Amino acid sequence: AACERALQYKLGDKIHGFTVNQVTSVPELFLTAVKLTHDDTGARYLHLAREDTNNLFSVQFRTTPMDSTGVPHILQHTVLCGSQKYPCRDPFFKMLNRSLSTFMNAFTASDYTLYPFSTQNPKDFQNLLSVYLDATFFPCLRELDFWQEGWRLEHENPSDPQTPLVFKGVVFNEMKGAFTDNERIFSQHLQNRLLPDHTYSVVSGGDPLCIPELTWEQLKQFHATHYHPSNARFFTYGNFPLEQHLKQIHEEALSKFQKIEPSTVVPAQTPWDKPREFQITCGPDSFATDPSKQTTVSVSFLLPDITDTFEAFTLSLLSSLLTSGPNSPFYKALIESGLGTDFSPDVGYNGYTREAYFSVGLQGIVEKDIETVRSLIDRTIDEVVEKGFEDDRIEALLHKIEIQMKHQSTSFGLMLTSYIASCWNHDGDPVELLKLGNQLAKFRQCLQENPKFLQEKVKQYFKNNQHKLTLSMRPDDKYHEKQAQVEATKLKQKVEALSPGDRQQIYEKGLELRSQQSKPQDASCLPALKVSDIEPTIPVTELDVVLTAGDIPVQYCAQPTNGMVYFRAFSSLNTLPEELRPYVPLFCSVLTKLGCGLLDYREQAQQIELKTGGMSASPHVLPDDSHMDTYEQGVLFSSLCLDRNLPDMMQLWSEIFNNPCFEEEEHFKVLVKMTAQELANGIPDSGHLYASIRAGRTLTPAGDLQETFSGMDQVRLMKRIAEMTDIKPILRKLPRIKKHLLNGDNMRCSVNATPQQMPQTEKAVEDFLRSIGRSRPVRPHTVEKPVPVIRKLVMEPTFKPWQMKTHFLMPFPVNYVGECIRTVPYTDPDHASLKILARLMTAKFLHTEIREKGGAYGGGAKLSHNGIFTLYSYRDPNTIETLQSFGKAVDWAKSGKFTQQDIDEAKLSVFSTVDAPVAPSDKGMDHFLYGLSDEMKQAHREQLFAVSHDKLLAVSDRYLGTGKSTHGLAILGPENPKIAKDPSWIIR
Ligand SMILES: Cc1cc(C(=O)N2CCN(C(c3ccccc3)c3ccccc3)CC2)ccc1[N+](=O)[O-]
Ligand SMILES: Cc1cc(C(=O)N2CCN(C(c3ccccc3)c3ccccc3)CC2)ccc1[N+](=O)[O-]
Ligand SMILES: [Zn+2]
């Protein structure tokens, strides 16, 4: 094993310019931590040796912006645009298609920037390490790359100098879109006001109104000050040998540098002598909600340095006990009181900054209740200090942590490096964050030695703490219009200030940029894997289907789950009256939360938290593999637990199926409003998903149901329900739904657990199935399709697809665009071609047109299992032009002007996605949900391998050409005059 070999490292070992400083076994995480420092530069290194073939690298820099230009964010984009060893244009995006990576990306936190990738191929790992090391340490930082990624002045027509100058840039629009999320606005201001004395007071990602203040020289200087290895933390994880990583890192990068003392320290925030208050504004919601019904207020407290790890562990658990779930004191005082709709953003513990902070409050407050909310926060703090916490809640909490520690995920390295970053950033010891057994033991010991331990902590940090911030936010109906006018003004000033020489240089550089964006260039300097590096076959999944409780099929899959059990049940929707369909998602979200039998909603929540890692239900439409107009509909019941709590888990499922408390009217109203609030808040962030779902709604029977379940129709339905004065007519629908769903008449189940736990599990499941009820479909055409377990699917053989174009009028500064095209299902031989084509179009055409030229944050094409080919954009400054580029993309595809190497790279990209690691808990789910056998997946795999140039041009013409297939279109974004005057567009 890797972690055992790492145990052979000794203190003082010299390896490729590094010295081993510490070797620590962490058996609760099955890993050995190795701490090293690079001798000449002093750069810190952490290697986590573990038997995991999905290896990860990251490099981290302490980046401390002193303004809101977004320079660290823009620099992060720009270093990926070309480097000394890989000077060609855009090494990073190109490597995405020359790799079998499981993850490739970068991001910018408030005061650090992190560059991680992961892969299961050791040669791929070396390739990516070289590209990453060169980008970060020796970037070209070309002026025009900065103009593309950051901001620039550009003529509306770059080759016409008589057209007006406008602002453009990828990050420019990226941040406009980020702050389309009003929770993100609140969150940004909270941090800026609470920590006003240094870097944390600015908008690290870039305030859109300040971004055009960034100059090329400021960008280069910021790299010089922060991208030195003495200011870096290097991280690797997995079973690939450490020696090779260290060799590259020293020889490629670190050997070129000497040690410095980086001018990058973040000083401590000096604590306030008295509390502060501030008021801010945000955008209106999408539903023209009255601003006096939409107030957010929160109260935040400054906490100690996160580098004091045990105190940080204490405060984190404390914050959870205060705010998590319907038994927490703040939930009870604030949420169940009906004072708001949900917690305010960043509720709980925030430890990404040098000093952590706790925050609590509400959104959805009527302005008149604001002073009551503030009062209740204070009163709740006083009560907790006096009474402390329930013992069984503390046990539930430690159980919750145990489940996190034991659960096996497929991206453990990515999770770990993100997790330790802020602590490491301020010279903390990341290894102490891995020693969870120690932290827990000391926490338990503190509780035992001092019965008022947590009460004392609450008094010290929440009652006596003068560094307290009250922040309130109210929507402004012209928030973004006001932003745009300020920008229009700023733009005008910039432009009128230009000399004739400036205007000429802006014109020439713009044409030079467009040229660089257009002219095909050689990428041979870049490393690459080959298609022959892709595995020919996949490891078979061993499962065992057992008919149980009579005729109910249960799928058993033995896996290394580390003492965890994962249970799923799938119950058909085929007998439910179709009028109840829209209410199934609501039914699903409250089913495990209203109480069951003798446990009221509070008792049930406590049991669920003490005995499980979660219990949920969700509605699903599962498209058939061979027929576009056939699907399966049902509800998925899902849960997980430790081995020893399996019986308790199934006891909960039994009571939930048999006696859910649908008379719980008051907690029901609370959940409805929480859900509606959260759905509305999530629209911008998933803007393109909402567009795609609307656009596909008229293309297949399933698409129509999917919009009902999770489209804008569903968000709107929840919003209406949440505003009703009498929710009784809705609540009375829940029993009608239970009648058709909560029984074993049309059910199948799955179990994932260790082989030695399987026997106990079969018993517990069979008992559950015998405890729920037993003894014709609403749709006239249903088909039985056996699995290579017989699924009963709906088919609508008279379904005819039709075209629709919908514009959702949204108070957004950017757009979200979707165009869906009906093409064949998964088992159709043309499907593999279309899948390759999607990635090809994305890489070769759409990314450049929509993002690089347009300045949209994202633009591409994808193909779903259902056979819907989707073209989309995300945070897009343009709507009509994007729709035009969708069309030109299909013309390009039809033209066949892509090479064999382009096709090979599209294959690499696609296989890097479909061969991504599956967790032990999820093995066999392709079979369970979609009825996809290994023989089907392998046939699909061979079709993907066989995809050729002539096949690609053929399917481009056959399905994507004009008039060949049915299209659907949708946009979320502000008013567009051209669209408003086109009668083929429905405005919503
Ligand atoms: C700094 C930070 C990091 C994380 C984080 O990455 N995770 C993921 C890992 N997870 C670890 C953990 C869970 C419970 C108790 C202690 C630590 C974790 C989970 C599983 C394995 C190893 C660590 C904590 C949350 C979340 C929030 C914050 N923060 O707000 O300050
Ligand atoms: C209670 C809880 C918390 C967290 C969590 O977010 N963190 C993030 C912060 N993290 C702190 C920490 C972990 C290990 C050792 C010491 C502290 C922490 C990590 C980095 C900076 C500041 C605090 C604790 C867990 C995740 C899950 C659970 N849970 O299981 O209910
Ligand atoms: Zn970005």
Image (cartoon, helix red, strand yellow):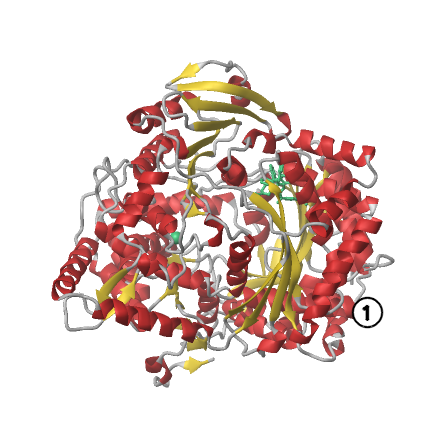
> Is residue 805 in view?
yes
Report the residue that reaches farthest toward the right. 598
Between 622 and 513, the residue placed more toward the observer is 513
Q: Quadrant of ligand 2?
A: top right
Say few, some or many: other residues with alpha carbon within 10 Å of mark 1 (under 14 / 14 to 19 / 20 or more). Answer: some
Hey, what amino acid is under mark 1?
A: Glu
In the image: residue 772, left or right of residue 977: right
Q: Indicate whether 585 appears above or below 564.
A: below
Residue 102 in percent (x, y) is at: 43, 41
Residue 562 in percent (x, y) is at: 65, 33
Residue at the (77%, 34%) spot, across then down? 446
Residue placed under numbered mark 1 in the picture:
663
- Residue 793, quarter of picture: bottom right
Residue 39 in percent (x, y) is at: 39, 20
Between 410 and 402, the residue placed more toward the observer is 402
Residue at the (73%, 57%) spot, across then down? 330
Mark 1, secondary structure of its residue:
loop
Report the residue that reaches farthest toward the front. 273
Residue at the (25%, 39%) spot, across then down? 83
Between 444 and 748, the residue placed more toward the observer is 444
Between 248 and 545, the residue placed more toward the observer is 248
Q: Indicate whether 463 appears above or below 291.
A: above
Residue at the (45%, 77%) spot, across then down? 809
> Is residue 773 in view?
no
Is the residue marked 1 within 8 Å of ligand 2, measured from its CB? Answer: no
